Amino acid sequence: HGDLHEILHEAVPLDANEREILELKEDAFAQRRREIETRLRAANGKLADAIAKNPAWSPEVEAATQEVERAAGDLQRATLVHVFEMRAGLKPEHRPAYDRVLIDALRRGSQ
Amino acid sequence: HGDLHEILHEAVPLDANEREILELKEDAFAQRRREIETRLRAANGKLADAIAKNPAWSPEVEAATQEVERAAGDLQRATLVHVFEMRAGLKPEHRPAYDRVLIDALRRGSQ
Ligand SMILES: [Co+2]
Ligand SMILES: [Co+2]
Image: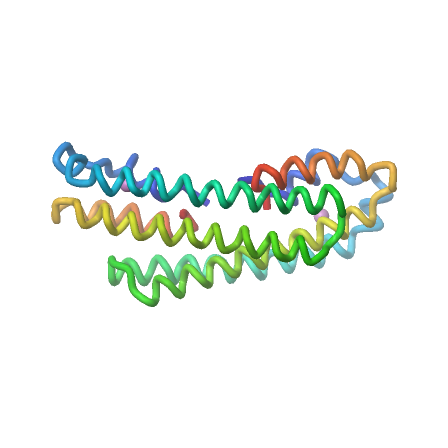
């Protein structure tokens, strides 16, 4: 229920200096994201394929849901790590607005 | 990326007889759903609380993400079981449209 990383960058955007300070970590996260999203799409495709061929529960369905679950969990965890990277690159006085947005979105299920 | 159960009921709604045949299983799923959504909200709240008090990675963050991941996986699995219950309660000649919607939505990541 919400793209946490995009919510943060939109609601409390980095200032000019912070954008420079975080450039490398933003690049590395964008790549990590992508990689995990690739795993996630493949897992969804495997689930869809299993069910298209055999429209019933089977061990392939159980396994594909486990694979989806873990890839989604991995993306949530990698995104949180990068959310803390961003917080580290903020001016300290900007952290309270950041925390307001972060906590509120987490409570709503944003990842 | 999509409420699979709602997508099915909207795109290929049950006919009058099928609605009657599936009434019990729809009631039981609505309840199971709710229960799992309760777990999910609590897990999100725990994650938000951990991070509101300690804005950094900790074992409480790791654990809360594991709890979210498993509750989301459980909801996906329970929803699939109920999706197969619905398919069982359809007239056989309605299953091809149902499968079209189901497979297409799964491929897109709907749960
Ligand atoms: Co960022
Ligand atoms: Co239903």
